[PDB]
Image (cartoon, coloured by chain):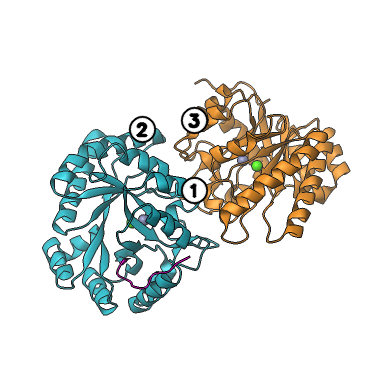
Chain colours: A orange, B cyan
Amino acid sequence: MERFTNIDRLSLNQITTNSWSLREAAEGCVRAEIPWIALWRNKVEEAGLAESKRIVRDAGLKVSSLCRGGMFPAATAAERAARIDDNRRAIDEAAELEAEVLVLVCGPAPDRDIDGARQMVEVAIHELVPYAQERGVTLGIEPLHPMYAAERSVISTLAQATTIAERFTPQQVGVVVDVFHVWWDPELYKQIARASGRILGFHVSDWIVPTPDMLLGRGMMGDGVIELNRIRQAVEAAGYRGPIEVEIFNQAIWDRPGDEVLAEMKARYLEHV
Amino acid sequence: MERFTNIDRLSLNQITTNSWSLREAAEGCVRAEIPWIALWRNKVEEAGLAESKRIVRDAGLKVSSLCRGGMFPAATAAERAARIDDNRRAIDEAAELEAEVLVLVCGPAPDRDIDGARQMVEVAIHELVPYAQERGVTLGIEPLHPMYAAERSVISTLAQATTIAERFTPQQVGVVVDVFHVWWDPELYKQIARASGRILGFHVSDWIVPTPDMLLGRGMMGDGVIELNRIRQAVEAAGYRGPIEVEIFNQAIWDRPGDEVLAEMKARYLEHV
Ligand SMILES: [Ca+2]
Ligand SMILES: [Ca+2]
Ligand SMILES: [Zn+2]
Ligand SMILES: [Zn+2]
């Protein structure tokens, strides 16, 4: 169980420094010698597609993931069509931004019919896959924590996302493992091994006791209860050699100037992850 | 699509009327003609074992569950022995109070080793079941929501509790289905059908948007997103003819005088559940 030697596999999700814009973020990651960055669609729209592309290409930055496509379930069918056209836009944004994986959180159920919303998710992805494969982008389903099933999206366990991804070849669809959303799982390592050759991303955070916020309760590594090194050795034995993003939703760490939190990021990425 | 015509299957868990004592609770349910009550160990110790039995024996009340045994994982072995001695004391309390099922929430992991804590849970239950069957009490494992995996207990999915219960006879150990802790599950109905002939209790609440508290985020039926009628028809097709407890953890419903909340309880038990 030895530690990493470089930060070449490290990546920085924009939302761990939500205070910063995209070019402030890029400056911060080259200042901290961080090679990989994960871009958010709202910040890219803030800056501009071509402008953001220039920003992170003259920083010499590689793009791990673009967040986030999805939000498939809607109350009616024209709304679903608009949502999957927004997913096509997100696909194009990932294509010209050279993103490795387009992260998909799929959307919550509009009513109480949760299984119907899951079926909507599956048919929407099956549809979206040709337009994704045409432009060289791969879609990665990110299972969320079951406490987000009512609010943010409907895929709640890793087994479910792996089942959805198994219908398509790994080059078309894969899964995204975030330790915050699935560390609790009793069948954690079994499902991780089952999803091997199909893992497209790895995000790291920690589960804090006690939870401050439901939507903003993540923290940085080493302060919570998750056994990070074990999970990521499991995901590397699963054949995942890609970048490792750290994605933290926390107000207390967002208010802090980003240089502090990127120093702490690298230090405890080398110590724990 | 059906409803209930009587309230003979309804039960009242003490903790949805946390303000009231045990004799206040018994008086409230005889005033409301509610036949079944579920008792908590702290209030029973407050009143006294023999006294509490007399209180609920001249009220003509039947007792569905006793809350709560468990808390098996501990940092050391003498501590685990003490925890299972307290579990023996809870078994005795359930036996002399004529409780149908002794509810077990199993306890959190002391460190970060969660799987070791799960192993501790199962070996503790395996030890505890002879002393339980001897006194005529049946243990019922209650799987909690995965967001409680860090804090309150370690069994987080229905499949896990059913797997633990399958080792012992249905008369020895069974599972407790609460819609708050298991409504999210993608394999909900499949695991419910798998757990048939072994369901010992049914708790109902609703998942509110947005969650007020993580540990006190339940509400009364009809105010959330849970498909209560579907889940309880699934567990009734599973052969569960026992009482239906309603267990709500909410400050907003705790402020109310208990007559209000038991009136609303019956109204929305017949209307929704
Ligand atoms: Ca993400
Ligand atoms: Ca309970
Ligand atoms: Zn993540
Ligand atoms: Zn419960």
Is B7 part of what is drawn in magenta?
Answer: yes
Considering only order in the chain, which callout, 1 or 2, is on the residue closer to the N terminus? 2
Q: Give the range drawn in magenta.
A: B1-11
Q: Which amino acid does label 1 sit on?
A: Asp
Residue designated by label 1: B185
Residue designated by label 2: B116
Percent from the top left, x then y, of residue B229? Answer: 46, 62
Q: What residue type is labelled 3?
A: Tyr
Which chain's residue wears label 3?
A
The picture quadrant for ligand 4 comes to bottom left
Label 2 C-beta lies within 8 Å of the nearest ligand 4 atom: no
Distance, label 2 to label 3, CA atoms, is 14 Å
**Visible residue check, residue A134:** yes
Distance, label 1 to label 3, CA atoms, is 19 Å
Distance, label 2 to label 1, CA atoms, is 24 Å
Percent from the top left, x then y, of residue B80? Answer: 24, 38
Front position among marks 1 and 3: 1
Is B94 part of what is drawn in magenta?
Answer: no
